[PDB]
Length: 125
Image (cartoon, rainbow, N blue to C red; front, top):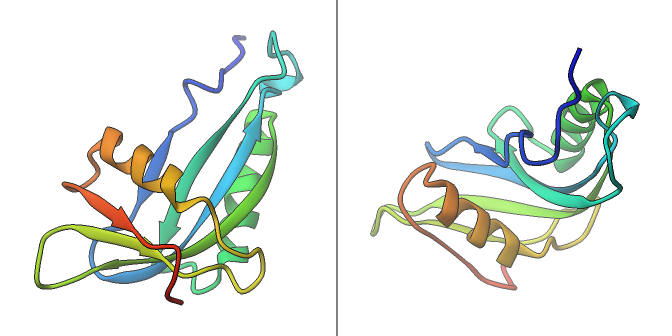
């Protein structure tokens, strides 16, 4: 057996084919209840099957807790690819958890290159 680590956790995984909802979840160091520290990091999730931010929070916290972690949605919002430019955008707020720090989402997604480039606004729905 080996312990996973916060760096090995998939950092971003999102759909890219229209308009769908997303969540930003913090993850604490507890893989297999044997991780060497109590550091934390955030992960970015959002998919067309999660018609509500609670669906991704529950699903993803299930996967993280199976690894061994403990987690919390900091907030959520909506993600929208817009026809006029390839770029995706991150905006709105979770009706259940309030606005995420969408600045994290843009930093994360731009680093991870799941599509091309992204932006945010602290507004919208």
